[PDB]
Amino acid sequence: LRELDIVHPAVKVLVMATEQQKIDMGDGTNLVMILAGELLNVSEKLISMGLSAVEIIQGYNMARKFTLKEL
Amino acid sequence: GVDIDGESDEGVKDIREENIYDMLATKKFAINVATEAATTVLSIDQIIMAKK
Amino acid sequence: AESLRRDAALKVNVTSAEGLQSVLETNLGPKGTLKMLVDGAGNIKLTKDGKVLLTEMQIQSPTAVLIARAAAAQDEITGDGTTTVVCLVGE
Amino acid sequence: PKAESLRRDAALKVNVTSAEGLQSVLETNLGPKGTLKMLVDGA
Image (tube, rainbow over all chains, first blue to last red; front, side, top):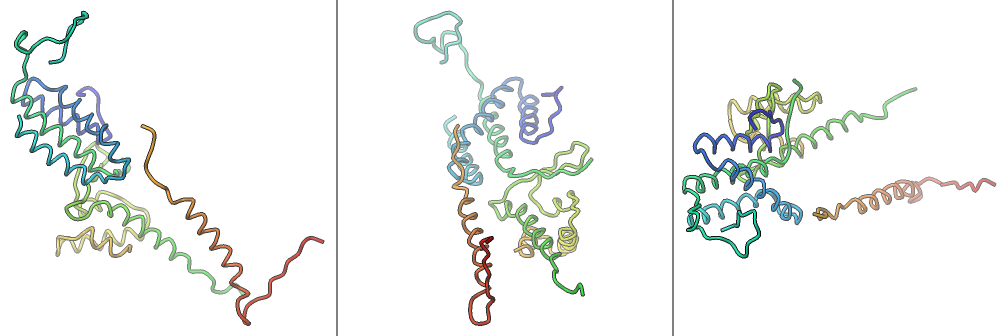
């Protein structure tokens, strides 16, 4: 991702998110890229049904606090 | 866990055998970054660019 | 004779207002959406504020130019409701 | 993943547009102040 310059924002955010994991920690660079990429793949079923992307974000925010509490 | 072996074996191993675990700083920090990464993509319904 | 008939230059202004409002219709209130601004040098600027949006885009249509220029004076005084003013003009 | 997105509404807008052109022609003969239509079969 460092040698390949990114233009489209969706991939560029994942590149900037990789630097967030790489600078603060020496492990988990592949954990962020794989997990964040699958969240958009499973979201295609909700986008198809007609659920707006606004309430989709609200669902992940409520699930994030429930996940961090179980960790 | 998940079996990482390259040879056919019945079942899977245990975490205590190879002592393969994930750190809290690696798992907890990766969740907050992954959620914010997919949020920006879902928040963009269109792009605006100009001529260079 | 060759007289009167059609003013249809109004149709361009009406269509220009619908296309401009449809872009800012996506982002409103706390439920709004994020947009990208590219200056051509490779800088990706992600901001929901319509004040920075209208300055980074260059529209050839004169209808959207008057709306963008008039919105700059309101942002220096009111400083809020940049998208709201645009949605009221197009609708 | 196949597709399900919209009912797309497009076949309905074509039906409305087809009725707009039909009324616009036929509304000219309405009332005593209307206009008289002519038909030619080619013969």
